[PDB]
Amino acid sequence: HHWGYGKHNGPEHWHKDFPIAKGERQSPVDIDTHTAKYDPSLKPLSVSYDQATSLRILNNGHAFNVEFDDSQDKAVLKGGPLDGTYRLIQFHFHWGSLDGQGSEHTVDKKKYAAELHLVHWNTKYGDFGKAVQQPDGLAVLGIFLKVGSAKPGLQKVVDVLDSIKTKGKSADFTNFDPRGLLPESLDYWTYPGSLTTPPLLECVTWIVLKEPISVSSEQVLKFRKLNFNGEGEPEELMVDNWRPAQPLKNRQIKASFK
Ligand SMILES: [Zn+2]
Image (cartoon, rainbow, N blue to C red; front, side):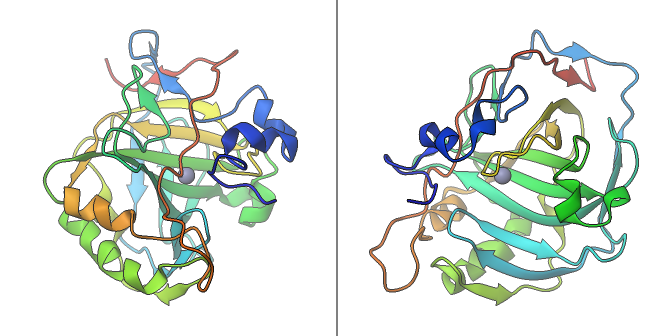
């Protein structure tokens, strides 16, 4: 049946429906900090999120997405390794059943409890659907979560999750400010990669921040109460919705910092 994260439809099966799964620039990857190359020509990231307009939160059956109005340049990413302007369309998380796993990227094989993806699309292609067909169509900002102190800016998200427990449920979610999810430093690693869920298209410039944010055990536990299934179907807890690291092959990871 349809792809997911279970024993019979999980990531090791995806290649049968999506051959790209075995492509040359698949994500995630392990970040080896000692062979990443410092690139002095990388510019600082420019995050302009002050005009962001969140609309809705949705359980799509494999994560929950917070969606933004992307019909104007209100929340944009630029700079770093990017050419041009990338509009924020949604963010989502990947997380584990235990605090020792959950991130998709790893750093010297270390796994984090969760990983936040802020997904942006290159405005020169007009809409998200065109952008995913281009090698420079998407920019995804990846932020690691470790378990520690609570993150106050995350609690608005945590409190609404009971309203979208099952697949297909959505809820109005206005006036959410993503600036509250960013770490203090914007130092990053970057490499060319793919979406980490089907259709696994190789259209992403990955920008992975060095500094994790901390969240409390109580906040991550509420992620684990969501459901893969629809209402009225047997209950399958939404945990371990992460793809394992893929071969780096002919790629260089660059770092903005030494
Ligand atoms: Zn993701």
